[PDB]
Amino acid sequence: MQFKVYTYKRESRYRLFVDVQSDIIDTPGRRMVIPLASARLLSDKLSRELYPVVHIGDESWRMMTTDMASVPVSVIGEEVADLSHRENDIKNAINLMFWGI
Amino acid sequence: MQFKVYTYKRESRYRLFVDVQSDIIDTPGRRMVIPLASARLLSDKLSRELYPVVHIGDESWRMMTTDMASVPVSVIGEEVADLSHRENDIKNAINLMFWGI
Ligand SMILES: [Cl-]
Ligand SMILES: [Cl-]
Ligand SMILES: [Cl-]
Ligand SMILES: [Cl-]
């Protein structure tokens, strides 16, 4: 579901992802997602506009916009958070990546 | 380079991709891309709005918008075509996938 955050069932580079696909775009068996990285050991120079900072589990995470990819529903684990309150920053980051605006 | 089409140097599910990242968004060592699939053996019901039809090498291809992903520059092979003349349909497909508009 768009803007919900899930854990991966299989080992991946990151441990959470946010679903960014529209809820009226049907791709059977898959969803387009963006991984979230723990902010703790990342560069302080990472653009906040392209890589928004969000809060889950009492810590900070960066949305790894440029590591967007689709996953099969078989890898979609437990839902751990909802980022719909950060739609503006998420939309801005995605649009920046393609359109530089 | 945005809207240029390249072959993969390593075996992938598809054999061409289009670079869709902005040319002023720098991700060192990587680019965001969308694979192209040969249209020949695909369903005739596949949405043209979400999966545009383009022409390369004297055949038709579908832009596999929902299989968008980043690749390392090490996998970027020869440039085989430029799809900048299809920017309107490419932009429409990408925006549809996230925003349903
Ligand atoms: Cl991490
Ligand atoms: Cl947040
Ligand atoms: Cl193919
Ligand atoms: Cl074309």
Image (cartoon, coloured by chain):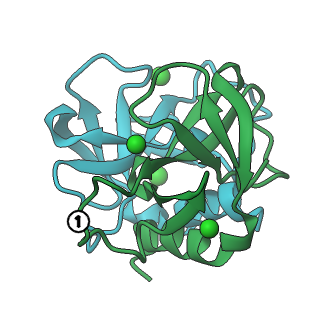
Chain colours: A green, B cyan
Going 26% across and 33% down the picture, which residue do you hit? Answer: B7
Local crowd size for mark 1, using a 10 Å CA cut-off: few (<14), some (14–19), many (≥20): few
Image x and y of residue B69, in percent:
44, 41
B8 lies left or right of A48: left
Vertical arrangement, residue B92 with respect to residue A101, above or below: above
Q: Secondary structure at mark 1?
A: loop
Going 36% across and 26% down the picture, which residue do you hit? Answer: B15
Image x and y of residue A51, in percent:
42, 66
Q: Write down the residue under mark 1.
A: B26
Quadrant for residue B25, please give it.
bottom left
Instruction: Give the residue type at disc 1.
Output: Asp
A54 lies left or right of B48: left
Viewer-side residue, A60 vs B41: A60
Q: Quadrant of the C terminus of chain B?
A: bottom right
Can residue B46 be spotted in the picture?
Answer: yes
Q: Quadrant of the N terminus of chain B?
A: bottom left
Image x and y of residue A28, in percent:
78, 29
